[PDB]
Image (spheres, rainbow, N blue to C red):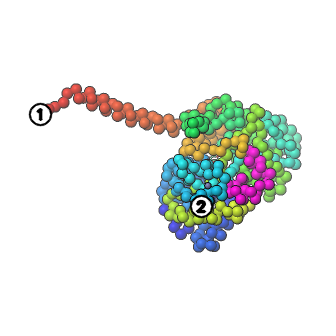
Amino acid sequence: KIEEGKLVIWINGDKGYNGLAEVGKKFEKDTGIKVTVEHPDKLEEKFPQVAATGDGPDIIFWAHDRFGGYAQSGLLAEITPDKAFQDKLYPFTWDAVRYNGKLIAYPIAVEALSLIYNKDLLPNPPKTWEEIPALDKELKAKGKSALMFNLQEPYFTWPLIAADGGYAFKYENGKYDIKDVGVDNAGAKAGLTFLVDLIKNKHMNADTDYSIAEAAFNKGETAMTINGPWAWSNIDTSKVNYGVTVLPTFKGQPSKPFVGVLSAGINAASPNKELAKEFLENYLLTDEGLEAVNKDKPLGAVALKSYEEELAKDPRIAATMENAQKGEIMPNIPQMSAFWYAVRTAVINAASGRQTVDEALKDAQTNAAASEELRKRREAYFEKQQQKQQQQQQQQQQGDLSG
Ligand SMILES: OC[C@H]1O[C@H](O[C@H]2[C@H](O)[C@@H](O)[C@@H](O)O[C@@H]2CO)[C@H](O)[C@@H](O)[C@@H]1O
Ligand SMILES: [Zn+2]
Ligand SMILES: [Zn+2]
Ligand SMILES: [Zn+2]
């Protein structure tokens, strides 16, 4: 319980928060209610820490994968859009924000990573990963590199890992299996190996992060990067002649991005739930609301039918979709937090050459399952204690005192 007269909204610093705030100023102008857009760091880690005290914003924006965990900890209010409003959004976007049969967020846009390339350096982009090392060496004769992307976040590395058969959680019998992690298999080991070889062989640098990769591409120093729709604003401004296309194949298989649906959840502790719903339904999720955000930082393939339709002809959104088709929409189950942390640690560890790919992926295999492991052992502990207590009492009733 923190606000009453106003809406505080959290969104990631790489998204169009300036357009979001514009929508806020329009909401204030019509309503009298002040809207404050914030973009703090690590907001997806910060939210569950602050919302569990009665602090935290009224509306949080993130990809849908985190919302399962938030919902499970009781942190999101159930949203109540009517059927008419639901028909305004593509059905599959609604499923991404369904947890235990309840709607826990409003979907905004579908996001997938793509290959972004400088047409002046590289008029034909490579179709496979395997040809990138030779391309990197060729480009050195011009003082350029082939490719730079964010190696610090497993999101950007996942598509190459999943290509030859890496997965998060096997879907089976209408259930995600959470002792069945696919980060340790041969296809995952082949993908990470190839990445680590690129790094060790100096085609890439292990400490390359989001902003270093961005700068290199937007200044014209690298022929390619890998990024989502949000990144296109800055490329336009740099004036680099760029195309957006299919991610390269690995071992003849498509790269498989983990697809995110940018979503808006309402804090369960918020005393402004109705204002938040009003804001989201009638201000943000309209052509004009999404136009404001989208013209700041592109959203991708938007959830709202009428506006997606207005953006239908953009070849960059087409490539986003093609990349989404070859990928999978992320699970939103509570275990996603642990999966990401485990894969982050493993990539960073293998990249720096501290652990082998084998050791690092085996470690992530354990780390991603360790939560359900603890739960199983906790159950067994109390069941065994109950058994011993039962058996000790039945043995103790070998004799009893009587008056
Ligand atoms: O790298 C792990 C990370 O991946 C995804 O986060 C993406 C997010 O979906 C995009 O909206 C964009 O902001 O980049 C992020 C990667 O830095 C997952 O959504 C997230 O839970 C996960 O930690
Ligand atoms: Zn700001
Ligand atoms: Zn309907
Ligand atoms: Zn090489």
Is residue 62 or residue 87 the one in the foreground?
87
Report the residue marked by disc 1: 403
Q: Quadrant of the C terminus?
A: top left
Residue 86 position in % (x across, y down)? 62, 56
Is any part of residue 163 visible from this angle? Answer: yes
In the picture as drawn, the residue positioned furthest to the left comes out as 403
Q: Secondary structure at mark 2?
A: strand
Is residue 240 or residue 127 the one in the foreground?
127
Crowding around mark 2 (Cα neighbors within 10 Å: few <14, some 14 to 19, many 20+) is: many
> Which of disc 1 and disc 2 is earlier in sequence?
2
Q: Amino acid at mark 1?
A: Gly
The residue range painted magenta reads: 299-323
State the predominant SS element of the stretch in magenta: helix
Give how far apart the Cα atoms at labels 2 and 1 are. Answer: 72 Å
Q: Quadrant of ligand 3?
A: bottom right
Left or right? Give the position of 376 relative to 323. Answer: left
**Which label number is shown at residue 9?**
2
Crowding around mark 1 (Cα neighbors within 10 Å: few <14, some 14 to 19, many 20+) is: few
Is any part of residue 153 visible from this angle? Answer: no
Is residue 195 or residue 332 the one in the foreground?
332
Is residue 202 part of the magenta span, yes or no?
Answer: no
Left or right? Give the position of 124 relative to 362. Answer: right
Q: Quadrant of residue 127?
A: top right
Q: Is residue 390 above or below residue 88?
A: above
Residue beneath the point at 31% across and 33% down: 389
Q: Amino acid at mark 2?
A: Ile
Residue 18 position in % (x across, y down)? 68, 63
Residue beneath the point at 56% across and 53% down: 103
Residue beneath the point at 31% across and 32% down: 390
Mark 2 vs mark 1: give the one in front.
1
